[PDB]
Amino acid sequence: GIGTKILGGVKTALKGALKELASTYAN
């Protein structure tokens, strides 16, 4: 229920936003 935070939320954030930001910082 609040497992959503460490599943659907944080793992989506690393999968999308950190993966895109770090990838086009490193280039």
Image (cartoon, rainbow, N blue to C red):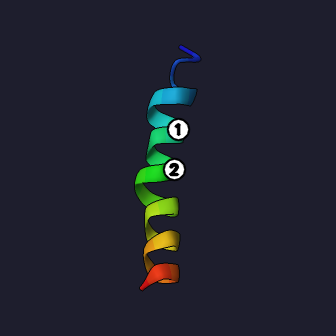
The residue labelled by disc 2 is 13
Amino acid tagged 1:
Gly
- Within-10-Å neighbours for mark 1: few <14, some 14–19, many 20+: few
Residue 1 vs 22, above or below: the answer is above
Number of labels in the image equals: 2
The residue labelled by disc 1 is 9
Q: Residue at x 52, y 81 (%)?
A: 25
Measure how far apart labels 2 and 1 are at the Cα level: 6 Å
Q: Within the image, what quadrant is residue 16 found in? A: bottom left
Can you name the residue that lies furthest to the bottom here? 27
If the image is split into quadrants, where does the C terminus sit?
A: bottom left
Helix, strand or loop at label 2? It is helix
Q: Residue at x 43, y 63 (%)?
A: 19
- How far across and how far down the image is residue 21, in percent? 52, 72
Residue 19 vs 21, above or below: the answer is above
- How far across and how far down the image is residue 11, in percent? 45, 40
Q: Residue at x 51, y 50 (%)?
A: 13
27 on left or right of 5: left
Residue 11 vs 20, above or below: the answer is above
Residue 26 vs 9, above or below: the answer is below
- How far across and how far down the image is residue 23, in percent? 43, 74
- How far across and how far down the image is residue 24, in percent? 46, 81
Asked whether disc 2 touches disc 1, contact meaning CB atoms under 8 Å apart, the reply is yes
Q: Residue at x 57, y 28 (%)?
A: 5
- Within-10-Å neighbours for mark 2: few <14, some 14–19, many 20+: few
Amino acid tagged 2:
Ala
